[PDB]
Length: 387
Image (cartoon, rainbow, N blue to C red; front, side, top):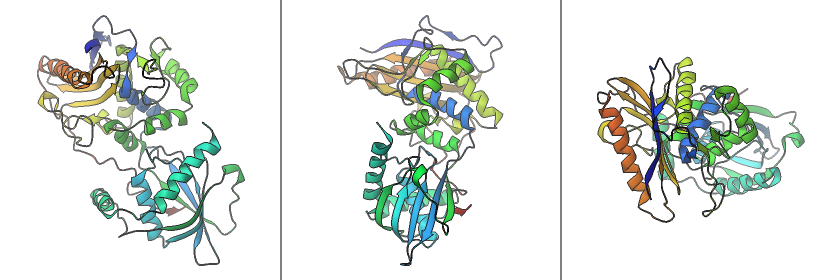
């Protein structure tokens, strides 16, 4: 069962600022991963698009010749394989190849994809597998080549040998007298958001949402920002994934109007810092690693957008650039993908045809100024630096 729940839009240049749409534009529907755009807005407002996550390494020489290292985490929600490979590269550039005790605190988050001890157990497990495995030359080579494109140098065939990896809480970490402290800054937040909104599992959005205070903080933010409450927008996580079962699902939900208000606000907060939607959201046809990279037709090169797919919904929202100006849009479809596998692709085609009509009946597409960015978790200021 594929059918329209709601479609709405507004011209960026509207003097009335009245959102246009069908009669369902003020009823709540599942959002799926367009939720990530709301999480994006929150993060931009709270942190700023140039914010960097400052992970600290406390490094102490051992009588051996080797090092102990304690990671004081910054809750960087994008510390994954790429970033781990870069850390290893950096350790080798700093002449560290052997670590005796590697320790890490509760703020050191790791994306291989409850409670503090148990969360840290999973990070430890992941770390121990990852650092005890040879770095894959094919994956590293591709990564080193992407890094060189943004002028980041990485080591040749890097490696690390770690004796032990343990959880040490921030409160119980005693900084050694002859430790050095080095900082490994993330790429800017806008870049992390770019990566998240191109294509991701739940991990980044969910960790951002928790970092910022979770649901109680989110509802206070939305009330302050939008004069909105839970009848406009009801979140349970940052990502929009199912928090229930297949039979009784629990999805983030919002009105079509709220999605437009989000896009407007996001656009405004970004412009204040000189940035565009296409700095944090995928560009149809241009962003090849995204869910809209194979979009063609009039959307190609003209459209900034985020996809969503859950059992009960297929969604799209963003901005289309037309000869009549930029236009914010959201389309929310109903699906029953658990019952009928064909619904996601059928829904997706109906959304594209709806957005193509929105473009084609507003004078046709006007290209945006955009060249495919590579949203790596580090940039040229990420190098280990003695702070």
